[PDB]
Length: 305
Length: 5
Image (cartoon, rainbow over all chains, first blue to last red):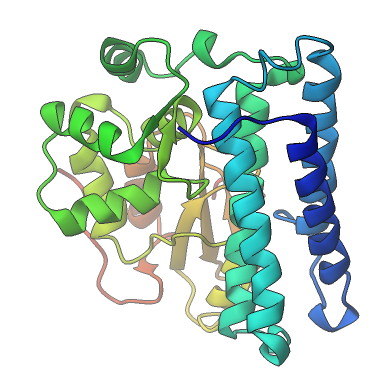
């Protein structure tokens, strides 16, 4: 594990978020004001940590001893530092849309949003609930508790091994694929929260990895760490090709899918499917004319089986 | 987000 968190540890990141914020208030950035919005996420995080801190009144060093939280505070300083190092080591090219240091900022924005979700799900009301966490899918629940008990968080390697025993992982490159599908906070730890989001998105547990294989590894329409505005912008190029669609993880309704597609009246709509697995949304969308050409490609995966 | 097609 990583070091003790004291009160002086937290003043550190508060100062670092401050520097991130002021850096993000640059007119030149022309920072769209929509989820994930770094300029809210950061204040909200601090806000939530005040909450956690104000509740660990006095016993402020039972908290200092929390593993998950010690990992979190670490990652947090880490991520905020990276971010600061982009504005430095990337100088001017922050400012062209579709440039490295600017997509990386979106990625970072994204991770930041995953962090706050993870935290809030582990500390609802600001008071630790990691080990009493309800996992959503019956069968995923079974696996986790029967492999990690009431642990909130494991290291990646640990998780990989455990998973492999039940759902073998074809290869090292695949493992690596999986690792960045599931490590939403990019911390080389898998948390119970992280695990639930993956297991919801890729049900039934029974065929978990086969599912993930068909919907993400081998699927032209899957998009990785992509935001809503990014989906609108990407599908611009197919505006004259209705049926063109992509899809991704919803950022605000974490654990759910967000399909984006071009209509015959020529707008670009986005839905969160409900009460169907993703498989069937996509099959029906094909069958019904709405989801025909993934990311523009004429060729569309057969999933009926 | 908007209703499924």
